[PDB]
Length: 113
Image (cartoon, rainbow, N blue to C red):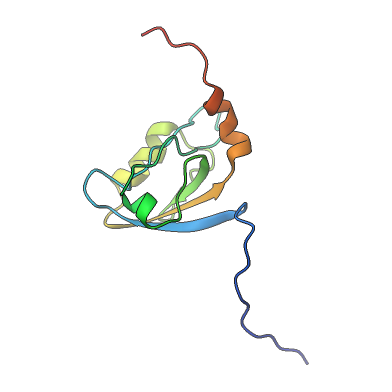
């Protein structure tokens, strides 16, 4: 004998969440990084005015987990992209605001073109 009722939303935007972005044209309005020893994907930037921004969900620094329904937990950069090229209009980008990780990318090392 037991039961439960609905629950109101709180905060703590740390865990992974859903970010349904409607491909406007250029893309979802957000970049992606990673693809090294499956370290994990992470947003590099978020277009201003895009769906990733407008939606008011996706944010720079987030850690892309899956796209639509693909486990990119340990996928390369391309793959993480191919998942966006294989998507469509309504792409579900499940990322988790994790700046602690992206930090690595934030620092960024050398790069003599």
